Image (cartoon, rainbow, N blue to C red; front, top):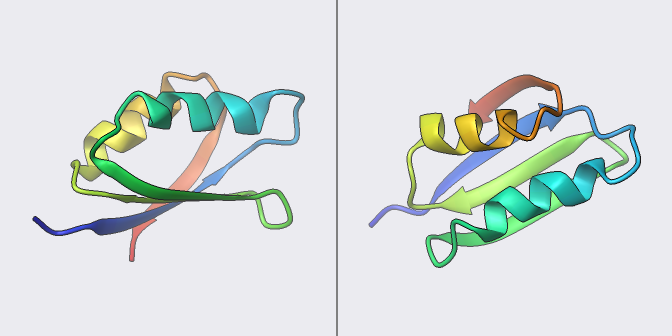
Length: 72
């Protein structure tokens, strides 16, 4: 199956916010292969076989502001 690369600008200028994002992604193992969170750029990179819309909805349901997303 394709391992897609999604990138999101997520506002994580808040205590616990990067961890909230990590957590929802851990629940989607074993079909999430890699995640990167950069506080220097406020970016979350997700490498996964799962659909974009599903990753986006799960990140949004953390209540953290998702400014934009891309498939790369």
